[PDB]
Length: 559
Ligand SMILES: CC(C)N(c1ccc(Oc2ccccc2)cc1C(=O)O)C(=O)[C@H]1CC[C@H](C)CC1
Ligand SMILES: [Mg+2]
Image (cartoon, rainbow, N blue to C red; front, top):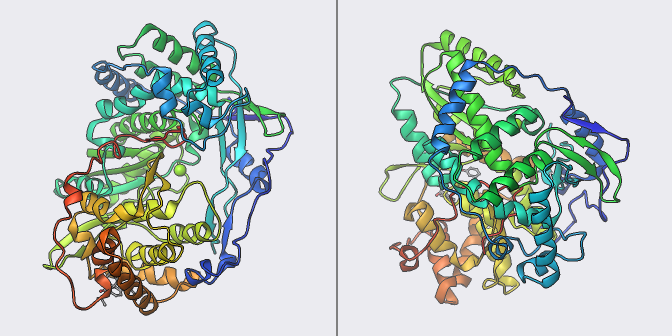
């Protein structure tokens, strides 16, 4: 069937949409070519709609069924709990889209009589009505990028706040613990960036002759079929579940996840969906399970040998035992055909990679640098173009989510996050006298509130003290960063070094936590290095819930 059907009504915005970067005195010091920076708007929605709309092809074989049963057996060990309204509400982000039933984010978290009473009625309804298609709103997502030698906005389909709270009640526990139980070490969201690298590097070394590749599925969400979603429900159903939760999953599956009507911001019937919705609680879990299933089965059809998968939603990377250049290329092609039959055709054709640093998964790649002692140290990085374009935009305008803070946390050891983002933002935060202020950001889709002053500890716990001393990066990483700077018009190292030394001095004079950031974060900038000993606060940090599972589109907030 058709991934989508359209009525003609347009996907409309719900206010004014900024497309260009504001000429700002502060954004200009970070990036000079402001015209290369842009944000998607509903004005490009038509272009997107045509790309995600198509008839899906699907043929299932014995390999698929086999892997499916393997997966179900493991799911069979699971015991999901079911959250009470109270907890599900606690999980709602303070700034999440309001409900059309008289209440909003704040009321939900505050457990207002009106919000809880409505939520209750939606839950009862999910228990009584097993059919009626649940209404969703479709919107053009606004995201920032740098022009290329432009991207049309992405679309998001999400149900009402009321319905979202119920999804949590019935599936929060499931989507937080079933992926790991079913896929084990292949589930990428259980790893912190450093743990992801270690898993990738060790996996790579465990091969006599390693061969690896990333697989890009062309619009993965639209390739998800009604069948894949029921197969996915079948996996969830192997769990021990409270009666009400079992019915909630059954009804939410037929009424929401397999598809339903599309309404715009004006309240107009836009069309219908018969593929994955991007703004539902099961999206990450669902996509990860389905990609792993098709991929694993695809590997068997292709005869790839000793495959180790690493899956994060629709993002996939496979590392296996080489069989030779020609044989690897043939196997890879066979893999792609198997995936195509399973309704997961490629966007970018896949290519075998014999160099670990050249494999990009989760928009990132593993690379290597050196610590003070001089020992090689592997770490996660990525092309900084987008991270930087967005740092510029968030500098010029107020945004709910600060990706820059999220990028500093996840890529702390990188040459670009240290030299550019830390310097730029600590300089700016000192000025505005807002170093104490907590900011929201996302990690694997879950929303968190973090104090910039804590970055030193956070970085030590997740990356180790070496994140403050890495130097001598790879020639490949250096060219990528440098050619990035030229493109966006970012000041060179010298300028940044001067700024960092000036910010570092200012941070050291304040003492307390600010001096902590001064000493650690900017030690790369001075010549007279300061001995960097373990930060006490790093040994008393609970950062486990940070890397448990994916939540993108889940409307998840970790208090
Ligand atoms: C060796 C030495 C001088 N050096 C480098 C300076 C420039 C560079 O590569 C470029 C080139 C152009 C633009 C940006 C970086 C790479 C390195 C390195 O450590 O290998 C450093 O000490 C870095 C160490 C990390 C900080 C955070 C910035 C300076
Ligand atoms: Mg893709």
